[PDB]
Image (cartoon, helix red, strand yellow):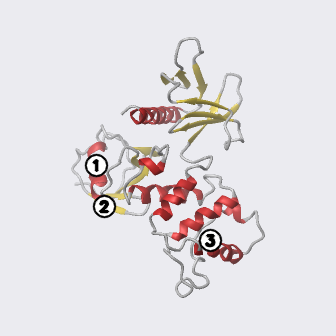
Amino acid sequence: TISVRVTTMDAELEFAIQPNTTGKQLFDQVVKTIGLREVWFFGLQYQDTKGFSTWLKLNKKVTAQDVRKESPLLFKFRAKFYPEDVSEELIQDITQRLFFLQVKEGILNDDIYCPPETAVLLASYAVQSKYGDFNKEVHKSGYLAGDKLLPQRVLEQHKLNKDQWEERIQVWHEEHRGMLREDAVLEYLKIAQDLEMYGVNYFSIKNKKGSELWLGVDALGLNIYEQNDRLTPKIGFPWSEIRNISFNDKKFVIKPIDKKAPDFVFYAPRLRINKRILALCMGNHELYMRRRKP
């Protein structure tokens, strides 16, 4: 058999399979263990040979696939597409604890811009759960010192020593008393889910006349951002307004809907991106559909 191990935002699964197993299968084996049951989001990431992080092929032999040769084998379990409205699409005490971690962890890296004011309300919630209600007896001083709760960026924008900040969080955690470590989260997401960068895979891209910038692919449609205004986009195209897309080596072709509107194409210097940009553009759009017409 094979010596494998599945990794989650919080959980560490281990496994074994004969040299046959495929993605799909494999996939399912974990999603089975973790009682998850809303899987049309998550997927499997792994370290290949070349040196990148990639998404397993459910429909192919993992062997066929070029996993970083070693042992045990190591795989990440990450939600691939995010939901348009968490509140109404997410349902398991687990599915949610599953995004939350991915999301949060991500913010704690400024991988998602987040303004100070709103930076706290989150952490105010990001703790509401971890410690449930506060305790002057349990949560004495230092209690939040062995934790991370704010994006370094925010820290350095204010002349507050670690505790000044902590001192300031305490206060809002207090206010969360009476909250079940469950809605603490939702409320946390319902908060985060509106940040600008939320659930948006990014890609750098080129036009006709050389200019460089960002492609916005996310469970809604697409967005083209200037080199710096990644927050607010400058052009957009929703999954309803696009009939087709694909690439030819380095070209990205997206067909609008009618016949009078030109043909949408841009330029990625790397292919794998296009291979992903597609993969992503698909799923997203596709997901977009069964939603509004099941």
> N-terminal of the two: label 1 or label 2?
2
Across and down, in percent, residue 221 comes to: 54, 33
**Few, some or many C-alpha atoms within 10 Å of disc 2 (few <14, some 14-19, many ≥20)?**
few
> N-terminal of the two: label 2 or label 3?
2
Q: Which mark is residue 28?
A: 1
* Residue type at tag 2: Glu
**Few, some or many C-alpha atoms within 10 Å of disc 3 (few <14, some 14-19, many ≥20)?**
some
Q: CA distance from mark 1 to mark 2?
A: 14 Å
**Few, some or many C-alpha atoms within 10 Å of disc 1 (few <14, some 14-19, many ≥20)?**
some
Q: Residue at x 68, y 73 (%)?
A: 168
What residue is disc 3 on? 172
Does residue 123 lie above or below 235 as drawn? below
Q: CA distance from mark 3 to mark 1?
A: 40 Å
What residue is disc 2 on? 14
Across and down, in percent, residue 284 comes to: 46, 36
Q: Is residue 263 left or right of residue 207?
A: left
Front residue of this view, candidates 33 and 258: 258
Q: Is residue 13 left or right of residue 18?
A: right
Secondary structure under the numbered disc 2 in the rendered image: strand
Rendered image quadrant of residue 121: bottom right
Q: CA distance from mark 2 to mark 3?
A: 39 Å
